[PDB]
Image (cartoon, rainbow over all chains, first blue to last red; front, side, top):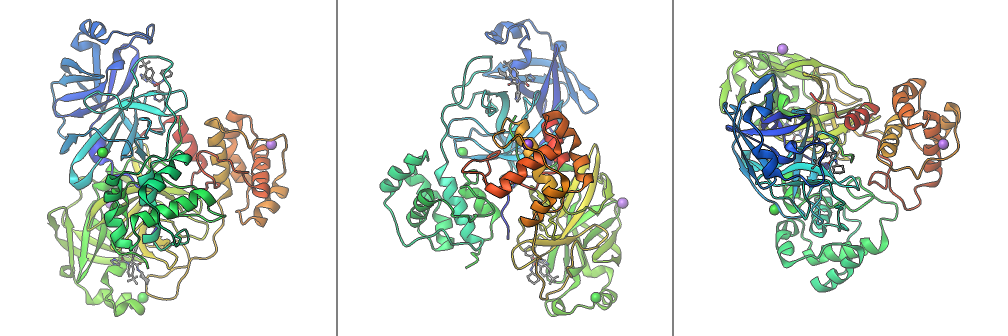
Length: 306
Length: 305
Ligand SMILES: CC(C)(C)c1ccc(N(C(=O)c2c[nH]cn2)[C@@H](C(=O)NC2CCCCC2)c2cccnc2)cc1
Ligand SMILES: CC(C)(C)c1ccc(N(C(=O)c2c[nH]cn2)[C@@H](C(=O)NC2CCCCC2)c2cccnc2)cc1
Ligand SMILES: [Cl-]
Ligand SMILES: [Cl-]
Ligand code: NA
Ligand code: NA
């Protein structure tokens, strides 16, 4: 029973966090095998954050201009290369704590755990979603760059996010571990801003299913809806379109609870129309959209509380 | 910037989780040096569950009745004893991953991180608070028993909770690591219920300070109050009393923001008496009470371990 924002256990990632210093700048790096991955903006100068040319900045660096510290041990940089917006520092020692891992680029709506770090040391762990506008609503202070996001389904760490910068509304932008930004953002000081965000409809539906699994049905109704009429209504509340792929993804939760996906859509339509009238759903007074269908099946019982 | 429900990094605790099996029952244990700690109810059968005599059940057990697994390695049990509601299994190997640690008993209102585990394998981490009614609003399925709650200070893990059981409303009851229950609960199948709960006032105030630090200010106002008048309001709305010690624990946030505690208390008084008027605070339509003042300072200052 119960339902929490639940992160993956962070130990496998903790053993990979290092500190990277270049000049007066320090941030975090990810040490896997004999490579340390970090944001290439570690080599941006303080005097020109507006139009750095990273090829020209990097060719001027020697290996010893990069200080990498793993706990109390200095790691010797023996080569470097840039891939998109990530710097890859080759070090002379492989991380003996490297977990089984892969790099994955995720789609908006997907969730992951974030291990927030400063100076190479972990501060805390929390759950995030890739928003439809390709930002994440993180909790990150100065020097958090190079903190990573990940999932650990079946003992393999899937790294999906590396933190690079903060945007003017206080949300966050970054890259996959190949250095390609999520969204249109760039790793320099610009006027760039997050676009209008929307609600991740398929996740709200997943969380309503979680509420039913955990024994709450008050928000259901006697109605159904077509998929197109649902999207016409939901989009008026700045909800993302629900696709047939999303409907398919919700199939297992629908089967477990006996509530057809389009009947749950009718419930959501009515909740958007009416509000909660002083009630809560899984402890919340708003509709939660940062649990995926996969997340709900991971956390909830396989037996509905009828 | 940003503000999230944040847990401590769990790696130091992951290295301590093992599986403990007694008869047909499996649950989790905590392996520190050469002792595994787990709920004593592991030795209960379903028949015993209604009226277990744990003294007699334990004497009937021997070391071989306990199967302890750390990953794939069996740990040989060489002794067994009970401390209150916790079973201690002496094993022949000291856990080489044992962190610096303490056993600490926490107070209602204090928060901690939970490493939820099944079959000795860590599954997830989340943050929660000890409620005033000594339950926790966890997320736990069958077999979660023996999962632990903790805080970290520098390099030292302070273990404060071991999970034992689920109450009928779906909240959770357990012990400190010396096996003393939090709250008026017993480890057997009987009529037991969570008492009426209250809201943790000092934590709501800490969260309002966090909101101000993060630029949410609409609820600030020109008024101040006294502790006595506010505590009459608190009682009316089923909030915990605010003590002078709470005001002193909040002192920093008051200075940093320019809102005296009793200034902020006037904000909270008006929110209780009038609601939010369709607005939110830090992305919530409810007043959040599971961040302590220390949680707010730590997250807004970036403390590491
Ligand atoms: C060089 C470049 C690309 C302009 C840059 C500069 C600073 C940082 N930020 C570092 O804190 C930081 C950088 N190096 C070590 N720390 C912070 C950041 O984004 N402020 C932005 C302020 C508006 C203009 C763009 C930069 C930061 C704060 C909180 C959370 N996340 C990051 C990130 C990128
Ligand atoms: C023996 C005793 C004390 C009565 C007991 C029995 C079962 C368990 N529960 C185990 O899942 C469990 C036990 N041993 C292995 N798993 C679960 C539990 O509390 N159901 C209670 C149902 C009402 C009567 C008391 C037990 C559980 C579920 C979800 C989260 N937390 C725990 C806990 C305690
Ligand atoms: Cl994805
Ligand atoms: Cl007894
Ligand atoms: Na010990
Ligand atoms: Na005021």
